[PDB]
Image: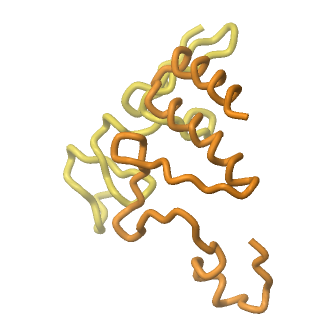
Chain colours: A orange, B yellow
Amino acid sequence: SPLPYLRNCRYDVCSCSDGRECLCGALASYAAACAGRGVRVAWREPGRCELNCPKGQVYLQCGTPCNLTCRSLSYPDEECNE
Amino acid sequence: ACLEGCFCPPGLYMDERGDCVPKAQCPCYYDGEIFQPEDIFSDHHTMCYCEDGFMHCTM
């Protein structure tokens, strides 16, 4: 149900010091629950708070955090049920 | 002393992520906690904020 995650935005954007990120930490509270049930949403734009991955990295929507870190190659036999 | 290494010009100060930045977005480290450049912040009795690197507390 989106109706509360909408109710919690209007209490955050009017209350906090910077309504820029308070907005874009509340919309993610909804996508993080939509994703916990199965639905991924593509809601990032240059206006709607796309994060700035550094020059080494690139933005990515749905990826595997198992073959990323250099510690993985040192301990490959470990399971990554992520 | 007057050491030798990798610095960046005097207008720029070193950030945690390898880049060095001016003192506008230079975070505060109050009580160990890393606060962002604009974080108004208070219990009931104290009143504290982070302006440009320093944590301006009052009572």
Query: What is the count of numbered marks?
Result: 0
* Image x and y of residue B7, in percent: 27, 60
Q: Which quadrant of the view contains residue A67? A: bottom right
Residue name at image x 45 percent, y 24 percent: A18
Q: Which quadrant: the C terminus of chain B?
A: top right
* Image x and y of residue A32, in percent: 66, 48
* Image x and y of residue A51, in percent: 43, 51
- Can you say whether A66 is above or below A34 in the image? below
Residues B50 and A3: in front is A3
Residues A29 and B53: in front is A29
Residue name at image x 58 percent, y 13 percent: B47
Q: Which quadrant: the N terminus of chain B?
A: bottom left
Q: Which quadrant of the view contains residue A64? A: bottom right
Residue name at image x 68 percent, y 7 percent: B45
Residue name at image x 63 percent, y 34 percent: B31
Q: Is residue B8 left or right of residue B33?
A: left
- Can you say whether A64 is above or below B58 in the image? below
Q: Is residue B7 left or right of residue B58?
A: left
Q: Is residue B20 left or right of residue A3?
A: left
Q: Is residue B59 left or right of residue A56?
A: right
- Can you say whether B43 is above or below A81 in the image? above
- Can you say whether A71 is above or below B22 in the image? below
Q: Which quadrant of the view contains residue A70? A: bottom right
* Image x and y of residue A69, in percent: 59, 77
